[PDB]
Image 1 (cartoon, helix red, strand yellow):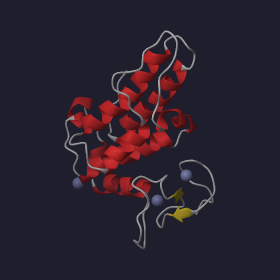
Image 2: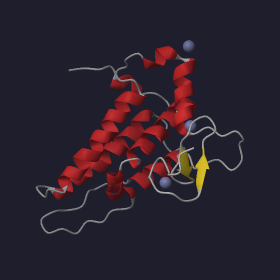
Image 3: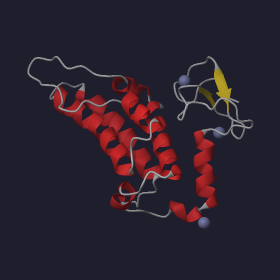
Length: 178
Ligand SMILES: [Zn+2]
Ligand SMILES: [Zn+2]
Ligand SMILES: [Zn+2]
């Protein structure tokens, strides 16, 4: 197994996957690394199994159809994995914890949102459709762009949204387009 967390790239108290060489901090994995379970297989491994059991699940889909899906166990897992892919980027630190808004010439968003809030909402089964999760994720970056206006810091929202969107298209097998 790797000697650093796959998510945050630090050493520490690491739980090792049994079916692949990745390792995780307890609360870096999503869901949080399960208490017992020998062997244990990471989310990467669980996602690869879904694909291998249903090869056709990689055929292109329309985003509108994906968003309307109910949050059955496989879709729950796919959203957890997509959330984890965002935390895998170090720039996610800006979006992880609860924000606050006091900048001359700007007003805070009407509905603040942040990654750890989306993480709690997934853990608490608060989303009934993929659409709920995707809308809260896109809201994080939209709030950031609107608040920061012409400050160059706006770019951090574009960057982390791009990571989200690329991973969304990969995980949910969105039909490729020009
Ligand atoms: Zn970690
Ligand atoms: Zn694994
Ligand atoms: Zn099949």
